[PDB]
Length: 81
Image (cartoon, rainbow, N blue to C red; front, side, top):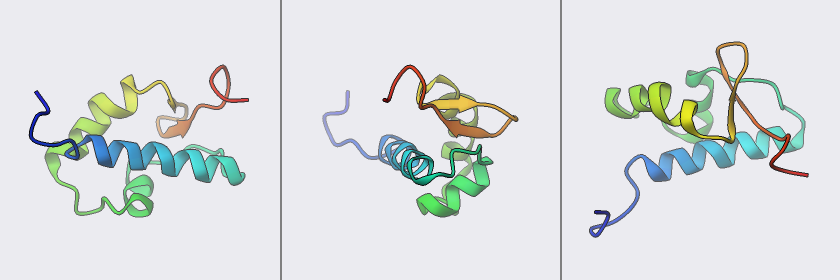
């Protein structure tokens, strides 16, 4: 269980969601590649483990993340008003 702490994966994912949410809020609701997200979220160095997990777990199961032109976008509809 997460008895020790809670940051690995979770923190980065929350920052990605928050980032996309904010960038989407101001006007850039357009989709963004995985790499484009890393930079703005300060997760360029990241690591193969997280990078892969984001691609084949986080940015696919996360409801707020909408897959459009293969890239990852934020989901406004049926969630935010």
